Image 1 (cartoon, protein in one colour):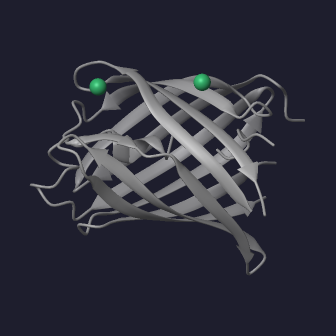
Image 2 (cartoon, helix red, strand yellow):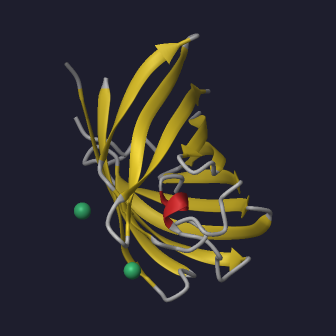
Amino acid sequence: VIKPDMKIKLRMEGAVNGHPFAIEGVGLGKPFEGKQSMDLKVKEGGPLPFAYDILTTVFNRVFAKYEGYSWERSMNYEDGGICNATNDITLDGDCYIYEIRFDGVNFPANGPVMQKRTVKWEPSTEKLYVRDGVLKGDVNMALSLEGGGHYRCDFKTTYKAKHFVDHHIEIKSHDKDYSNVNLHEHAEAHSE
Ligand SMILES: [Cu+2]
Ligand SMILES: [Cu+2]
């Protein structure tokens, strides 16, 4: 029911520090090869007044090597910024559809997110475990900063269907104000 080549269509509606925006994207990935890529367009609220990197992990764990589901996530940044995100994932033929909501608050004006001083997420390892019959996933994430140094964030995801996973996520290309972004992720699961 999961095919070697699958398409992705997503819409994100969100806000950061009260400023609303929306983004649409199309892409394709290889579930069993643990690869995906996509092109993302800002439809509303552009040009975004915050670092695009806080969105990238929100833009599917089926894309990982060795009815649908949904997930909720909290991303707690070390300087007090909090982001909540959800994704409802459904399957339509050979096409995954993501309905995504994103909401961030309390990012300081002088911090690296609002001043767009972030470069990339360092590769990470998500720890997945079951609790109350649903799957949780925690990870310490870190954004690399332009002036050297790192910006810590704690991720807490709940997966709900209707070991480790190594992640690497890169923005391969973007225009000046990030209205267009090409985004790429690899992911493998392991254990012991
Ligand atoms: Cu760049
Ligand atoms: Cu690649």
